[PDB]
Length: 184
Length: 189
Image (cartoon, rainbow over all chains, first blue to last red; front, side, top):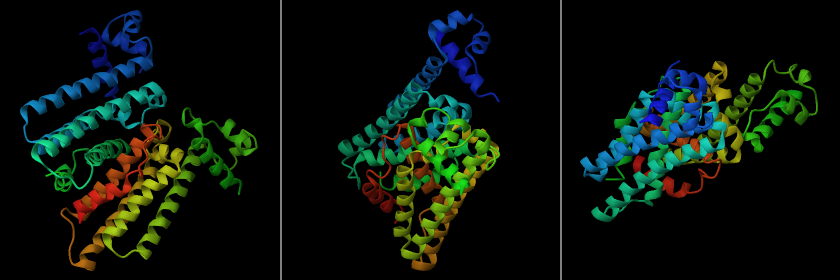
């Protein structure tokens, strides 16, 4: 549970209005112990992205187990992403690209992997609806999946851009009414 | 015109492989053929330079949207063209898109952040105006309120542009625009 405690404390600090040393003192350990898990600040943020991706996928998989309807499953995965963003504005800023760190390539590459994993999960759900339920979409599932992912990323971007005033979940019911019409 | 050369050179610096780091007045000075101190005589700060650039982008997009209103009268064809213009503009100006997609250097400065928000508000209002005329032109509206739909359309554009920047410009927004339109049409027809 060592590496997670550090990432948890990192997440907590990002949500407040960061330095390896400051985080070390925060979790209550030497800088050497911290550097053993994350040899550098970039590796630390890279680890935070992985920690976020793993937590989100664990929840997505739970939605897959409990929800059988492919339509509502897409809806829940979207609502989960928007709700998570909304509740973690500091994390959303680094994900949306409004953070300095986004300049670092391996960190950007890493964020891309997280969005691609989410997008893949959406495509998977669409493919199942297509093949198991016989649904015929007006376009390739990859295009529908990109639009769904685009709507989320655009909500997250506007949320940061507006200094966190325009909520990601605002009008989701209305957006979903239009998006779902061609998924149903 | 040493006001346009600076904004022009600035666009290039952001447009070059310098998307990596931050631009400096020094490097910008050399890229314009002058001194740092000489640059600060036209713009009190680098932030004012970015704001002049946002201004340019806004004038460019608003002008192109004005022409769409004049050249196309069908509501859906007008939406298609504005969505296409926004995505096409981003692909033609990768560096400029980085600003609009967000950047620490951009949103930390409250005047530049507000400015970028005005640009998006200008776009959103144009979309809202287009959607609103459908009721009087064809006697019908949309499955959701026009203000909500304008925000949804803008959101898809902002999501595509973010992905474009994030993937280091490997994902091209217009790549499958024709199929994206077939899907969007069916949803809002």
